[PDB]
Image (cartoon, rainbow, N blue to C red; front, side, top):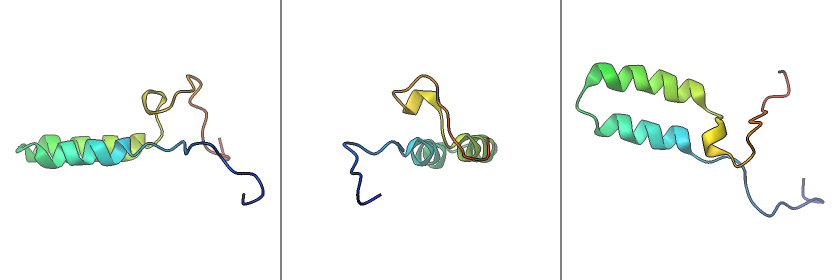
Length: 59
């Protein structure tokens, strides 16, 4: 970790972005549906330059 530095951090707060969007929306139902979806999405290809989008040691 410390021994090998990184030029940039790969972990865009898109989920936080979606959450903020959901908060702004008056619709409660949409807010809840989007909250779980966005929360569940977490890591996505759109928010990462690499098209592979590989993540998670377990799978």
